[PDB]
Length: 406
DNA sequence: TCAGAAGCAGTAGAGCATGCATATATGCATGCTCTACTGCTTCTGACGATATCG
DNA sequence: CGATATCG
Ligand SMILES: [Mg+2]
Ligand SMILES: [Mg+2]
Ligand SMILES: [Zn+2]
Image 1 (cartoon, rainbow, N blue to C red):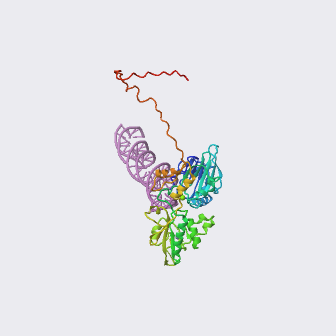
Image 2 (tube, chains in turn purple, cyan, green):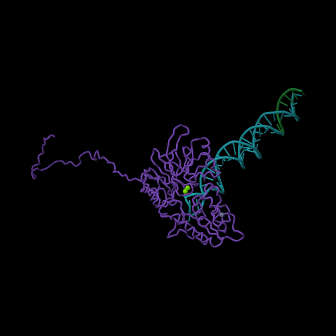
């Protein structure tokens, strides 16, 4: 999910990954990647009506994001309003107002996120300092020190705020394995399965639309088989991905999707209508790459687990784990840090108190001096009546006199 | 006698929300409201012929 | 034929 309101505190004139209610007054739109939770309001009728009444508002995103977005027929009205920006290329954006001729320049830099085709970061630099928006990123430990654009002369830049992805910001997802390990496990399993007979097929229950192209491409390169998907016209301008997918159902590896694909697999049938070739039945096994299932285990588990006679689960996460998030935020050391999404189990307060010790808040101060005036006793209640005998005791000490005047 | 006027019920067309599981992406499906418009049913009253009285 | 009151 995306708990972001698509509006930074430093630059409220730009909205990122959210165009629902208050972002209709923004001067520039930014899109991290092409996931549905980061595209709320992008197809709204009010936004459609606003686009046809303005000329200076644009939608900035990665070129791969533009290719994936313009392929959908529902978003083709953005064809003349999308401006793609290369990664690691500092460009100047003009936040010109429509009504008044006022203008404001800001410098944005796109950084790779390693999440899905077209996923990038947004690094803004303007009058209110430097802010960073890492929407659904994935960085291993020790990789934050390798980003060239986040360093200024060998040291980390002065970052004011970080709107980081906190999908797995909880002690349950302590150290998620790298995607290479899950890839190797899935490759070994699929090889050992399909190497027996040409009728052994492997399903890949991939929930997200984008993010699993790495697995498909590497399985195709290591097995020579082409994965089956529903639609592949979206990758028509991406040769390195298009030549690994196929619409034909006569392939072994499959990654097709369907709302009722579970019952179909239970009936020994892929999501595609084909259930057998040449009237010879097919032997199907299901591999579901996910991460939330592994975050609920109670003992030592493996990357490739077997939950049934023809069912498997793989730990394939496109989100940074708790340790990776902590390492990234501690290396950046920003003034503030806001969670974009709250975990299902965790709440807002726990994520906030986890992220706070990592922020650059190393500034303490002694409490303000509370004055003490007008003492709480006016009259001397401890006064004596001065009745004595004056003979049992020695003479009183005479009052001293001091005439020195410096 | 009957034209015309209320009064009420149904729908098109747009728009929006939520429910979906151990997924953080679902997009996808589904089901609801709103508003203007049309049609049917019930009601009313003026009206003209024609009955009746002079 | 008046023209008044029905009655549909
Ligand atoms: Mg997303
Ligand atoms: Mg994402
Ligand atoms: Zn298929």
